[PDB]
Image (cartoon, rainbow, N blue to C red; front, side):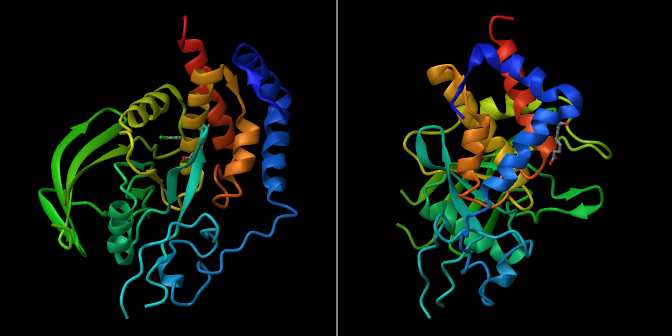
Length: 289
Ligand SMILES: O=C(O)c1ccc(C#CCCO)cc1SCc1ccc(Cl)c(Cl)c1
């Protein structure tokens, strides 16, 4: 289970795709079994005081990698957010993978952003999809909105074909310097029926949202609804692009098995697993052709 050279990768995708995606199925099964023989605790996630802070009952934040909110005078569980640090290529905690914030966790969400020096939000969901509530709107439709001590001001919006870029200016009321630029990359193209037919617009979304990262800011916050499926998909695509650039190799299976110890279910389906491969195929074939 070493890194596949970039030249042999598109060839490898053909193999994985053949015989009704048998190879893909084996790999994804191996990913699902990577969790086996591993008891990873998520005690804070399961605490009665924290249960209302979780979007889904079964989508937990592993204790060891969980993002801790600075404590608040009084409660003991005021440190909890359903979020985990996740590694990137050759960088620990390059991301914060989190759920789409609830109405009740808006203050927590925005406090985590401040405390972690987060400069980029990657939103991979629509608020409502196929008539179902996926994420609550945590940012202002226009101008300014207040979430605890974080005052959020919408500065500009660029609505592209498949994604929206919202430039915010954030401020802490308890801080006297107390102003920060936060950019949100929102992937908006979600079909009524079916699911992502093309990898090229997602690849463009990944490249642009990734290049917007500022040195040496905090981790890039990536969320969808549960913050596992599309979040995992983004993290792998982005990390593998970095690996390709640095050493012309790809390690999808190895990297995914590793991040799965950091947040439960990152890359939730075989379809998302296959999608990772298509995005990378597009990136490889795109170079020199
Ligand atoms: O919606 C799903 O959960 C989902 C379900 C299936 C597929 C597939 C496939 C081909 C295999 O048949 C992809 C996605 S998500 C695709 C995606 C969109 C936007 C971004 Cl920014 C990223 Cl990173 C990934």
